[PDB]
Image (cartoon, rainbow over all chains, first blue to last red; front, side):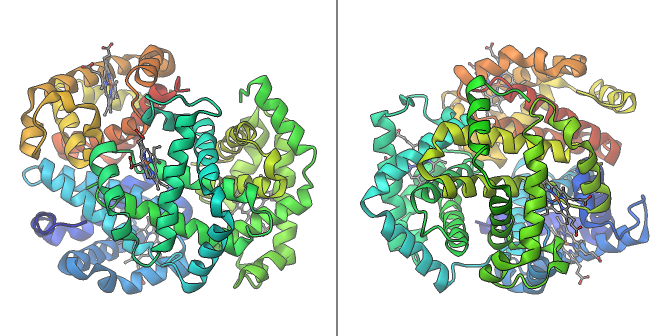
Amino acid sequence: MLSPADKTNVKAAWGKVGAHAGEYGAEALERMFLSFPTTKTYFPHFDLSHGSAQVKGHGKKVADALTNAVAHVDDMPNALSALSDLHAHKLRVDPVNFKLLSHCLLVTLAAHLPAEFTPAVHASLDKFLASVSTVLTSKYRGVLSPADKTNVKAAWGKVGAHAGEYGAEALERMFLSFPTTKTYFPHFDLSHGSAQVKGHGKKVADALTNAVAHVDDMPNALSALSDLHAHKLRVDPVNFKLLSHCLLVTLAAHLPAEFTPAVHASLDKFLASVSTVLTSKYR
Amino acid sequence: MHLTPEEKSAVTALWGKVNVDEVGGEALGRLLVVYPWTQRFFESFGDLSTPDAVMGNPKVKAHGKKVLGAFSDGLAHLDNLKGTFATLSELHCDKLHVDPENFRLLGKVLVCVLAHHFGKEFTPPVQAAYQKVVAGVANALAHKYH
Amino acid sequence: MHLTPEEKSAVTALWGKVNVDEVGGEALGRLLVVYPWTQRFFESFGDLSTPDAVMGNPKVKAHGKKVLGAFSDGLAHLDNLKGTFATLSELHCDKLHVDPENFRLLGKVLVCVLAHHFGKEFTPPVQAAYQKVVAGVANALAHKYH
Ligand code: HEM
Ligand code: HEM
Ligand code: HEM
Ligand code: HEM
């Protein structure tokens, strides 16, 4: 998460931005609409022509919100609480788009801060924008509610002793459906029935079992595994979403009565939380 | 798009057993429940407040049927997904303003629904073939965005 | 890769001003600093302990030159990226076990590096053209994965 040196780097960079925040915010948007045209689907009510007052005023609003974030770097969820509500309940922009605007903001700063945009500052600014994006999307579905926790414990209870079997199936579904994931297992026999896959599936399942048992203290229960993925195995974070989907498909195929729409939603939120914890120490 | 003989056979085999009405309404409903920001396109459908309200909503079921109906016709033209969906791609961009990420979210939910409905028959190789098909259909629907 | 002739010229014109060896070393070093999990392939390269050590590592710079040299010759074949990169795709999959997500991360870092190098010259339409190209190259390098 944002270290104090990260915070120092962002403060210095944004201070140099200074009175140009608004102009750079407008440029970042323009870059985004041009490079990623699908983001225009959220603004069909604007004149998106170059230099338009709507794009300029929106850029200033975005830049001010970032300024607020830089000045309250230690209390971001609180400083941006109003904006997180607005995007979650009213604007409902798909979370993938935040990565697109973050990239365009980073390109804009690079183009305008030759002296300041060093490798370490680049790293710090990317982390900062990721954290902002995370806070702004945090209420789309929110924390695990007591109803979610109940649904997860109920479904996993029904999994019971088959947890290991289901972990192996999920891996097999992943390797077939998303072949790029096989790049992390060059030392495995990945054929159907492989004992290496079954042994690994059981390890993965056992860890999920521990996570369910510690659902209110998941970061500490999963700490050694977070260390291991972040500093040794170093699996790209995108891959956790693919295994999560394949675990959900496995549960759906084995739990005809238990896999209701509500339990589906709760499980998807639970596996995203597990995925978050497992990638929390990457950077 | 290219599918191996094995993959095409698996897709068409399972789809012959799919009631598009029933699966279509399940898939769209679960989309709105699991990824609630997708509700932003359906303000006129009424009450989407709770999962039972969403799943029971007759406009959700009707719209779901329409969508998987169009998907179904797409599986008749697997070799030319882009040409098949061109007109609907333009509609979704120019008139409806739908972020194409929503097509990928629908794809994920549809795979889950098939697995739920068919159980053990939705084997790992069958899933992998459907994964190719739902990605191809989403790419086809996003093709004319600008 | 279908770029407009305007986009092609914009990509070509800027690339003529690039010091491939310097930009290649810069792009790969920033990749390893900003997304440190990509260091997993490079443990034989010696000291990667600080940003300064990464950026100053002669093995990182040499690999950067190699990678961007291949990128650079690819720019002469914008209408046939898949064929140009076919054998390299197979090597990265079968022998090097590189997750194709890494090509996308390098793409993002290269665009940042170009913006840093060229400042105002790196305009929003020029960036948009380079975004298509880095996506195009990443897709070509991932094409033979199986
Ligand atoms: C760093 C990320 C972002 C920040 C800090 C941010 C912040 C803001 C702020 C401050 C407002 C105005 C609130 C008000 O006037 O009450 C706003 C509005 C809005 N945002 Fe976000 N935003 C971000 C990302 C995005 C993304 C990625 C999109 C879509 C691609 C988006 C779409 C919108 C829309 C459609 C509006 C309303 C515009 C209007 O009708 O005035 N936002 N944003
Ligand atoms: C639901 C998310 C995940 C969980 C709970 C999880 C957990 C684990 C566990 C428990 C281990 C074994 C640690 C030990 O040796 O004691 C492990 C190892 C490993 N994981 Fe993860 N993992 C997850 C996702 C992933 C993903 C997405 C990939 C790659 C696509 C991955 C790749 C690996 C690799 C390569 C190993 C080492 C295999 C070996 O050499 O035995 N993991 N993981
Ligand atoms: C599997 C992908 C999809 C296909 C094949 C598809 C197909 C269709 C069809 C056949 C129509 C009828 C349009 C007309 O009457 O001319 C339609 C309309 C519509 N679709 Fe899509 N669709 C898909 C995905 C989605 C998704 C994921 C969303 C949004 C989350 C969406 C939102 C809409 C909306 C808002 C309408 C208009 C309904 C109205 O008249 O109020 N579609 N779609
Ligand atoms: C635009 C993207 C890329 C291009 C054009 C490219 C190109 C190349 C070339 C030309 C080689 C030499 C192969 C040979 O010896 O015949 C190579 C090797 C290699 N590449 Fe890639 N590459 C790219 C991205 C990446 C990335 C992002 C990574 C990993 C983070 C990576 C990791 C490697 C490794 C580990 C080698 C082996 C080098 C050695 O044996 O010393 N590549 N690449």
